[PDB]
Length: 212
Ligand SMILES: Nc1ncnc2c1ncn2[C@@H]1O[C@H](COP(=O)(O)OP(=O)(O)O)[C@@H](O)[C@H]1O
Ligand SMILES: [Mg+2]
Ligand SMILES: [Mg+2]
Image (cartoon, rainbow, N blue to C red):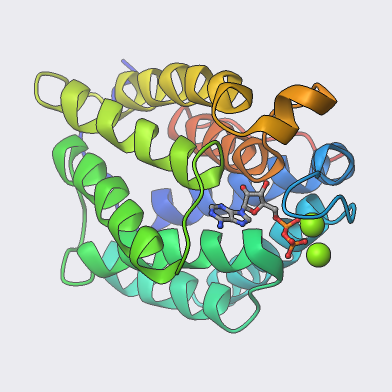
């Protein structure tokens, strides 16, 4: 009754919009977690402003064609990327959207492959990648996506599993990055990414994030 076998451009737009709203609602929390590389209190603000730049382009130029919608989202992120986290987020989504540029809709396997493509783009963009960060969480989420999509057609079930595994990775970040364990926090960039992913899931279920 509620399975998602294909994601068109409007469903992707909904994922973007609900992910952006969920991040906005949690931006102050994500800011306060920020300790790496400097505790300058801005991860949530940076990611929120970057995501908002993408969301605004999407809201003004919707399409049934997921590839075209992805081009619109990607351009918005890339012209408004703020801070280390916003730049990395924009590169994750640049690679994700490039992977689907020629599609009108995608299935669960192409969704998983697009997460992986985003990870590859983001790691290549960062000259000195550090583990325990948004890169680690994205990498572990994408590996989970590939494994699960191999026998899961339903994108809701797939995204639920991605979130379980992304949360496990996020909770493991202090075991990779010393300052996180010393201060007693998880990685702020990774937390912001989880906020986006949890909005993706709401949209796949046809639900909306309540605006704080
Ligand atoms: N070298 C790096 N490798 C991977 N992720 C990084 C790196 N540097 C920063 N990050 C990510 O960026 C987050 C901090 O984002 P942000 O506060 O926007 O950065 P800044 O304020 O230093 O520009 C970190 O929690 C981490 O997820
Ligand atoms: Mg900063
Ligand atoms: Mg910061």
